[PDB]
Amino acid sequence: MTDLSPLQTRVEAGIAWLVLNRPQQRNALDIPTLEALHVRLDACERDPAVRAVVLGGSGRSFCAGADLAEWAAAEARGELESYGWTEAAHALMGRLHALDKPTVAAVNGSAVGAGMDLALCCDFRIAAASARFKAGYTGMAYCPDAGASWHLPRLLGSEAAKRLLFLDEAWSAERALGAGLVGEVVADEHLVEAVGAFAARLASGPTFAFAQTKRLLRDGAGRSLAEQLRAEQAA
Amino acid sequence: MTDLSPLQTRVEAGIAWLVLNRPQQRNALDIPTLEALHVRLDACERDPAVRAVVLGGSGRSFCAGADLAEWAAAEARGELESYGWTEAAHALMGRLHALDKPTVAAVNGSAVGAGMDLALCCDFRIAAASARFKAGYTGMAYCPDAGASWHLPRLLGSEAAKRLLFLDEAWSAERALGAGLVGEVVADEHLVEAVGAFAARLASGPTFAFAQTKRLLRDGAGRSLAEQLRAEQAA
Amino acid sequence: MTDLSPLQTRVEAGIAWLVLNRPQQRNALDIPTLEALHVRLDACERDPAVRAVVLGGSGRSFCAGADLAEWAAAEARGELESYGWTEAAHALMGRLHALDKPTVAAVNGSAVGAGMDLALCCDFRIAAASARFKAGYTGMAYCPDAGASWHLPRLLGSEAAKRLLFLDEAWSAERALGAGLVGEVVADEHLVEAVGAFAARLASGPTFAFAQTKRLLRDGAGRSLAEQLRAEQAA
């Protein structure tokens, strides 16, 4: 039972569960949701209790993307230029992607556009069989492709990323699993149990070493092997 | 029935078909072919009618690579230094790879060396079952490895790319499909039909959004996620 | 029968076999082993006889990683700061990774930490079915992650590399094969025979062209396609 918080947060045994909680809107991303998760993520980094972070959706869908109704209100009347959704989303994507704790995305349902980009910023992705994935061209709209064009080619290769972006069809959890979009697929009934077990052994490990390792993985993409070895001879 | 054009071009329903047309030479690449496709590609970018581009071969083979006979004539007598094949090929590879329209390579037959590099510059690759792929060491010769050494590790991973380049064996369409070299494999009888259907739904989508997305995919490979998000807050 | 050399070296038919030879320590890496392989590798580059290089382990294991006993002696008494193991290892990893000859890693047994990093610096990896792979968190210790954080995401993708580093479980030869960690898996009884046959056809090819190609593959990762083509119009 929710208390109208935009983001339901619970911390159990070193695992911080951050669940999007607008199930009626399929957990559509709006500025209140963006900012709330953005501030709660900063609290998780500083908190010594949390050693792993889970990002999940409520109800049938993980996240349907940007809230078109909120965008409509700014567009239809008043300040469309003062609407700061893109600024709030890009700050959130950057922080989650570089978070110093191990992060897991529990794709309980469909992830679309910015909703899929939110899962791609996590280190791991476990998806339910019902989960469906949409990006770029939807058939009726075109999602923001900033983070998709950065994440998708790195996880899927260039061609596979262009099939998902340019074609309007959604990908199933099986197809996402086979293409490398998600790392693991479980039945929807066992998803919360599967994520908890996976996040538990992540939480049992040395969080400090994971933080340094996660920074080396990210920094290593832009430097040669010799540079990477030089950089690790320092701290 | 051909009209001696080095490149047979037809535009149907927003799809520009560019077919190499030297079937006797297995569509070997020479300066006339390089330049013709090079100029026709520039016309496709500017043309609002074309919304997808197909690159195919004639007869049994997609492209056997550089025309050794043309190179022999320049080598055997006269100006081997004035031979500008490498300059014409590198200009073509760069333009095709960065083309602002969705590009599909219909690998109707074997692609060797620069012929394979021509297909790698396309966004998508659909191959017939008869198609065979050769790169680097052939057993009797060594193909230009400039574009291969750039494309192959990005599509196949380092080791798989080195197996194809250092070993003289050709890869089948099945092996190319499994390694990520091509995205789809169909029977040779259904190849033209399969490419047309795939290029049709690409042509039905928003071409303008694909152009911006294709530029973001390419630019995103050289910058971090935070930089990519900064860059997309501008146009 | 060994002669107490830290590294057993034999050169047959253009193939230089470099076998770690401390089977009692599971071929644990210490400064004498690091330096010996480091100097022998430099001899292989200069030697025109060797056209392919094989790196193997002795006995049951390929390499168990850094020698903890040697580190203990420096730590327990005397000069832990003067201990130059990291410096010797990083010089070895850099040279092997950029070696001008084709290199093959014969993973005869388990490779752990720096031992796995040694195989990742080779161009090819053929593993026995008994081979097991450990990286990062072991359950009781945490291996150096400098080269792992550089190699593993490039071979396995980000998520798969983080599963191997953050989870303490080892990967089997089958799982390593399926994830792209090794290129080929054979029975332990046929490993030496399989590596010899693979290294033989590598040794039969044009070694000079492989050297230029191997440099282009490595340099191409940091530049665009247009830059790569500009660079190959020169030597």
Image: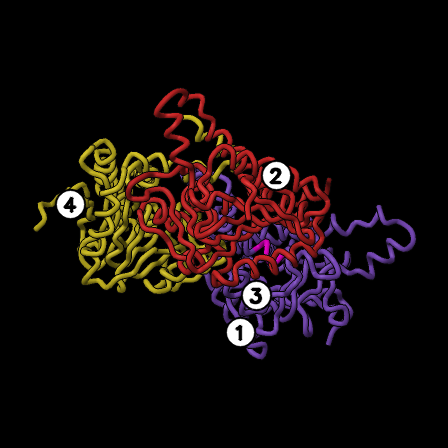
Chain colours: A purple, B red, C yellow
Considering only vertical position in the picture, is B20 above or below C226? below
In the rendered structure, find residue C8 and report the number of the disc placed on it.
4
Q: CA distance from mark 2 to mark 3?
A: 58 Å
Are dots 2 and 3 on a single chain? no
Amino acid beneath label 2: Arg
User: Can residue A231 be seen?
Assistant: no
Quickly name the residue at label 2. Answer: B40
Secondary structure of the residue carrying tag 4 is strand
Q: CA distance from mark 1 to mark 2?
A: 49 Å
Q: Main secondary structure of the magenta part?
A: helix
Of residues C76 and A145, the one drawn nearer to the viewer in this rendering: A145
Amino acid beneath label 1: Val
Point 38% across, 34% down: residue: B69
Circle 1 marks a residue in which chain?
Answer: A
Read off the magenta span: A161-165
Q: CA distance from mark 3 to mark 1?
A: 20 Å
Secondary structure of the residue carrying tag 3 is strand
Quickly name the residue at label 1. Answer: A186
User: Can residue B71 be seen?
Assistant: yes
Q: CA distance from mark 4 to mark 1?
A: 48 Å
Q: Quadrant of residue A57?
A: bottom right
Q: Are marks 4 and 2 in contact (CB under 8 Å)?
A: no
In the rendered structure, find residue A15 and report the number of the disc placed on it.
3
Considering only vertical position in the picture, is A56 above or below C30? below
Circle 2 marks a residue in which chain?
Answer: B
